Image (cartoon, rainbow, N blue to C red):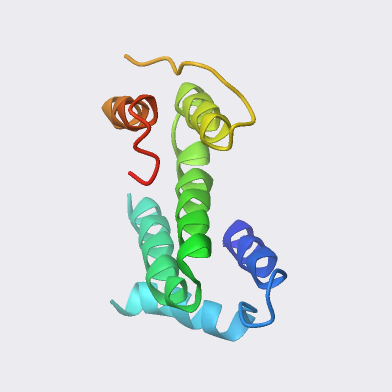
Length: 122
Protein backbone atom coordinates (compact mmCIF):
# COMPACT_ATOMS: atom_id res chain seq x y z
CA UNK A 1 0.00 0.00 0.00
CA UNK A 2 2.81 2.42 0.79
CA UNK A 3 4.50 1.68 -2.54
CA UNK A 4 1.28 2.12 -4.52
CA UNK A 5 0.41 5.40 -2.81
CA UNK A 6 3.90 6.78 -3.43
CA UNK A 7 3.50 5.86 -7.11
CA UNK A 8 0.14 7.65 -7.20
CA UNK A 9 1.67 10.79 -5.70
CA UNK A 10 4.46 10.68 -8.28
CA UNK A 11 1.80 10.52 -10.99
CA UNK A 12 0.03 13.47 -9.40
CA UNK A 13 3.23 15.51 -9.50
CA UNK A 14 3.19 15.65 -13.33
CA UNK A 15 -0.12 17.47 -13.85
CA UNK A 16 -2.48 19.51 -11.69
CA UNK A 17 -5.40 17.16 -12.52
CA UNK A 18 -3.73 13.89 -11.46
CA UNK A 19 -3.35 14.59 -7.74
CA UNK A 20 -4.51 11.78 -5.44
CA UNK A 21 -5.76 12.26 -1.88
CA UNK A 22 -5.37 9.65 0.86
CA UNK A 23 -9.13 9.60 1.48
CA UNK A 24 -10.18 7.97 -1.78
CA UNK A 25 -7.24 5.57 -1.49
CA UNK A 26 -8.34 4.32 1.92
CA UNK A 27 -11.92 4.13 0.65
CA UNK A 28 -10.72 1.87 -2.18
CA UNK A 29 -8.81 -0.27 0.30
CA UNK A 30 -12.06 -0.65 2.25
CA UNK A 31 -13.82 -1.51 -1.02
CA UNK A 32 -11.40 -4.43 -1.31
CA UNK A 33 -12.99 -6.02 1.76
CA UNK A 34 -16.52 -4.81 0.99
CA UNK A 35 -16.62 -6.66 -2.33
CA UNK A 36 -3.67 -17.34 1.11
CA UNK A 37 -6.06 -14.71 2.44
CA UNK A 38 -3.34 -12.06 2.61
CA UNK A 39 -2.34 -12.80 -0.99
CA UNK A 40 -5.98 -12.50 -2.03
CA UNK A 41 -6.26 -9.15 -0.25
CA UNK A 42 -3.10 -7.86 -1.94
CA UNK A 43 -4.22 -8.94 -5.41
CA UNK A 44 -7.67 -7.44 -4.84
CA UNK A 45 -6.03 -4.21 -3.70
CA UNK A 46 -4.02 -3.94 -6.91
CA UNK A 47 -7.10 -4.72 -9.01
CA UNK A 48 -9.35 -2.24 -7.23
CA UNK A 49 -6.77 0.55 -7.17
CA UNK A 50 -6.29 0.20 -10.92
CA UNK A 51 -10.02 0.03 -11.62
CA UNK A 52 -10.85 3.07 -9.49
CA UNK A 53 -7.92 5.36 -10.36
CA UNK A 54 -7.09 4.57 -14.00
CA UNK A 55 -10.22 6.47 -15.09
CA UNK A 56 -8.56 9.70 -13.89
CA UNK A 57 -5.52 9.22 -16.17
CA UNK A 58 -5.06 9.65 -19.91
CA UNK A 59 -3.90 7.04 -22.44
CA UNK A 60 -0.17 7.47 -21.86
CA UNK A 61 -0.38 7.57 -18.08
CA UNK A 62 -2.83 4.65 -17.99
CA UNK A 63 -0.33 2.43 -19.81
CA UNK A 64 2.52 3.73 -17.65
CA UNK A 65 0.51 2.94 -14.51
CA UNK A 66 -0.42 -0.51 -15.81
CA UNK A 67 3.22 -1.42 -16.40
CA UNK A 68 4.27 0.14 -13.09
CA UNK A 69 1.73 -1.79 -11.03
CA UNK A 70 2.47 -5.04 -12.85
CA UNK A 71 6.11 -4.59 -11.90
CA UNK A 72 5.45 -3.47 -8.32
CA UNK A 73 3.40 -6.63 -7.77
CA UNK A 74 5.36 -9.27 -9.67
CA UNK A 75 8.87 -8.09 -8.76
CA UNK A 76 8.27 -8.79 -5.06
CA UNK A 77 5.79 -11.63 -5.56
CA UNK A 78 7.74 -13.61 -8.18
CA UNK A 79 11.31 -14.92 -8.28
CA UNK A 80 14.41 -12.94 -9.23
CA UNK A 81 14.69 -14.32 -12.78
CA UNK A 82 11.15 -13.15 -13.53
CA UNK A 83 12.14 -9.71 -12.24
CA UNK A 84 15.32 -9.56 -14.32
CA UNK A 85 13.43 -10.61 -17.45
CA UNK A 86 10.80 -7.90 -16.95
CA UNK A 87 13.51 -5.31 -16.31
CA UNK A 88 15.31 -6.36 -19.50
CA UNK A 89 12.02 -5.89 -21.37
CA UNK A 90 11.42 -2.42 -19.96
CA UNK A 91 14.97 -1.54 -20.99
CA UNK A 92 14.35 -2.88 -24.50
CA UNK A 93 11.05 -1.03 -24.91
CA UNK A 94 12.49 2.22 -23.55
CA UNK A 95 15.47 1.81 -25.96
CA UNK A 96 17.77 2.24 -22.95
CA UNK A 97 19.22 -1.30 -23.10
CA UNK A 98 19.35 -4.39 -25.33
CA UNK A 99 19.24 -8.04 -24.28
CA UNK A 100 17.50 -11.40 -24.44
CA UNK A 101 15.48 -12.72 -21.47
CA UNK A 102 16.01 -16.20 -20.12
CA UNK A 103 12.93 -18.11 -21.31
CA UNK A 104 12.24 -21.61 -19.99
CA UNK A 105 7.67 -18.11 -18.29
CA UNK A 106 5.44 -18.23 -21.38
CA UNK A 107 3.98 -14.75 -20.64
CA UNK A 108 7.48 -13.26 -21.03
CA UNK A 109 7.89 -15.41 -24.14
CA UNK A 110 4.77 -13.78 -25.59
CA UNK A 111 6.02 -10.31 -24.67
CA UNK A 112 9.29 -11.13 -26.41
CA UNK A 113 7.36 -12.38 -29.44
CA UNK A 114 5.75 -8.92 -29.43
CA UNK A 115 8.98 -6.92 -29.17
CA UNK A 116 10.84 -9.00 -31.76
CA UNK A 117 7.92 -8.50 -34.16
CA UNK A 118 7.82 -4.76 -33.30
CA UNK A 119 4.28 -5.19 -31.94
CA UNK A 120 5.01 -2.37 -29.54
CA UNK A 121 1.44 -1.38 -28.66
CA UNK A 122 0.72 -5.06 -28.12
